[PDB]
Image 1 (cartoon, rainbow, N blue to C red):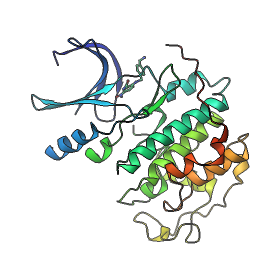
Image 2: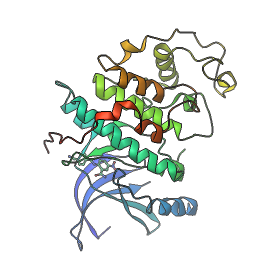
Image 3: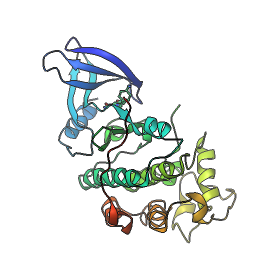
Amino acid sequence: MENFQKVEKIGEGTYGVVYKARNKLTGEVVALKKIRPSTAIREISLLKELNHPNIVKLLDVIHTENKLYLVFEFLHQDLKKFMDASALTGIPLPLIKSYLFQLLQGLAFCHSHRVLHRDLKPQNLLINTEGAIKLADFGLARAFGVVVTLWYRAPEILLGCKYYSTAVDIWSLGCIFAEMVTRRALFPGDSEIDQLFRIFRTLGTPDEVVWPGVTSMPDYKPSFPKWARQDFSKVVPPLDEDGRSLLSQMLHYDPNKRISAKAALAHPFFQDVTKPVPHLRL
Ligand SMILES: NCc1ccc(CNc2ccc([N+](=O)[O-])cc2C(N)=O)cc1
């Protein structure tokens, strides 16, 4: 890429190295990802049309010299860094609420267009000085696929389900909502089984009553220990009942009972939502 001046290396993405770069001709500042399949090309190309204010814009898909580069809209900070920076005092509830509401709008939009993220985490939620938050890397997982953080993975994925549904994104977002509130990851597993068991220890080992079909999942074992569900008021204190109610619906075990993004937007928790200005030190 002789058409971009590398300004800085902003990460080691899931697919490749990412650079903050400036377009020599336009002056535009972008995030350039070097990806390490014509099916992938056509699919990625479709994402260029998936435009929404809460979705990081995919500006270009460059396939030259038999290499693949994705050019994305640039934002100055991610939520993981913001949460660390706000760890001492915590992100104020009004801003947590604004961010959750905006992320749900982004999910509702993508899901309505049959596009899933599949790997939502604080690191791919980007923020700016105007109080906006945007989802990055939507659709890349399906376009490709095959240390990885497991903290936000839905249980159906951990249990080996081969077909993901929009519900996996709602689960991840619920885990992020909980982390913004408590200032600690909800389920910081360090292996697939530790991740699964951490979920079970908090929400109870699932059974056929709460999750019809769970015992027939590919990686389900009757030998799983049976833990009782913890009182929800102990999981994300001191979040209010509107917040706990919404979170509980985002963390239902059965993907089909899990609340949709569209339905979550209507939850009473958002009755007083506003759009505060975060304090960003760049
Ligand atoms: N102080 C460096 C710095 C610059 C920008 C960001 C947030 N922004 C991103 C992070 C990762 C990535 N990434 O593709 O891995 C992209 C962006 C993007 N689109 O702007 C975080 C840190």
